[PDB]
Image (tube, rainbow over all chains, first blue to last red; front, side):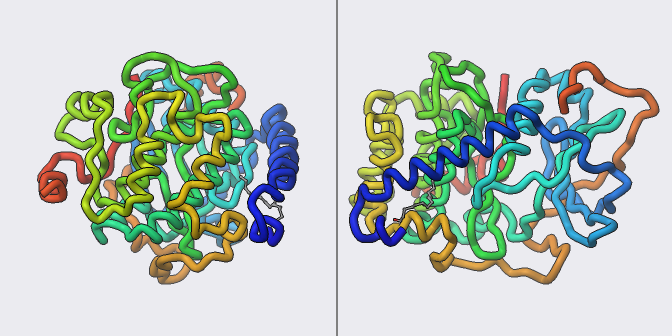
Length: 350
Length: 20
Ligand SMILES: *C(=O)CCCCCCCCCCCCC
């Protein structure tokens, strides 16, 4: 990291070695995934932290240790009905195999008659979404700090042949050190070729997803462009009341920037929000290096970000263990476990 | 302003993930 600090390029062999060792670690766990590492009665359910169409996330307390966790609970019958079996299997298999400072850690997983359970590290600082909407927008150094963590995270994930496919402020948690923790791997997939599933979030969808063309990891780089724009502007580059109107704006090949955006920021965003795949940054011959070497990131010490040595723009308020002040309130519902096993064959490998 | 138009829109709250 001093070597990198001295001159750019002298760390290329070192970064290559890091990712190679990281792939070895990942593949061992990918090929033989962990199963059934906890059970429901080992936790006290405290409060819902988030909801979805087929599940919810709850703050739980591990009875034996006293540690707090975020438990994702998925209704097996809901998953099947919404045709999300493979996606859910993808999520768990990938999560138990990855290891990076800006990804939320899966601690335990298990299933019962009714539900699938993924127990994650609890990140009390709340979603970036909540802070972004409240404050309005982040300054460029603020946004850059977060952007850099995503760049490194995507460099990691893509090296493992993983596509993330759901980047948005809602899926980015702020930890006690002010750093990003990426959550929700529901659409994550290990894929070497191109893929075709229409999934993600309307505002963040790359044109090639919308146009049903078939796509690769370049969609994550498009999504980064959307994220950086939304962080710095306070609103996304393409917004409307309905998804249909949003998709039309995305495919038009036209973006307008706020007057306060720096020249460097506008240039980076033109290169990330590029409809032409043969021109989009992150997808060229130099790959991620085109982004990391861009003028907007000139002040960014990439190794220091990874080592978490850079002072964060803000540290979220923490009222001790189990504090949910940084999360909104949700309707609480009793977790019901059936006496009959639901969808046993479908979720055998979970 | 674009900001005002955003705040007046129906998509300022948490955005659900979509799939077909
Ligand atoms: C300093 O210049 C020595 C070079 C060694 C760098 C290895 C440190 C870890 C690399 C972190 C980058 C993250 C890749 C996703």
